[PDB]
Amino acid sequence: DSIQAEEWYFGKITRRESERLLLNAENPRGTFLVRESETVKGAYALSVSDFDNAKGLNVKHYLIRKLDSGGFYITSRTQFNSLQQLVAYYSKHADGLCHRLTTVCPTS
């Protein structure tokens, strides 16, 4: 219920560590996690594995903005009341991302 209970929530890990976890060649395309942003205080980052036509296995990082008035978004036109809801939504369809979210990042 709290974000801290969610298996895809890794909290305060670095961008480099997110890539280490996500770049496993075993992870399906759209393997993901959510971490605290290291660039924007109080924001989150959605880190997603991908297979790029030119660069092969790569990780894409999307900034999730947090509103003081409540709510989260990658883009202000598609807002959610929780990170849980945002994850559910992007798990259904890419809607802009490199791929829909498919697999919770296996751990380390």
Image (cartoon, grey):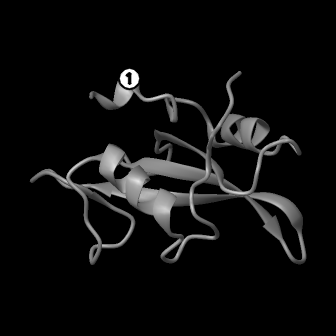
Closer-to-camera residue (9/100): 100
Closer-to-camera residue (32/35): 32
Quadrant of residue 22 within the rendered picture: top right
Q: Quadrant of the N terminus?
A: top left
In the image, 17: left or right of 87? right
Q: Position of residue 61 (x, y in %)?
A: 59, 57
From this view, report whether residue 2 is shown above or below residue 72.
Answer: above
Which amino acid, by three-letter code, is at mark 1?
Ala
In the image, 72: left or right of 20? left
Q: Residue at x 52, y 35 (%)?
A: 8
From this view, report whether residue 95 is shown above or below residue 104.
Answer: below
The residue indicated by pointer 1 is 5
Q: Quadrant of the C terminus?
A: top right
Quadrant of residue 75 within the rendered picture: bottom left
Q: Position of residue 14 (x, y in %)?
A: 61, 35
Residue ranking furthest to the front: 92
Number of callouts? 1
Q: Residue at x 39, y 60 (%)?
A: 89
Q: Position of residue 31 (x, y in %)?
A: 67, 48
Element class at badge 1: helix
Q: Residue at x 89, y 45 (%)?
A: 25
Quadrant of residue 79 within the rendered picture: bottom left
Q: Residue at x 28, y 27 (%)?
A: 2
From this view, report whether residue 94 is shown above or below residue 10.
Answer: below
In the image, 53: left or right of 40? right
Give the class, few, some or many, for how many residues have Cα within 10 Å of label 1's Cα (few <14, many ≥20).
Answer: few
Q: Position of residue 73 (x, y in %)?
A: 32, 62
Closer-to-camera residue (66/83): 83
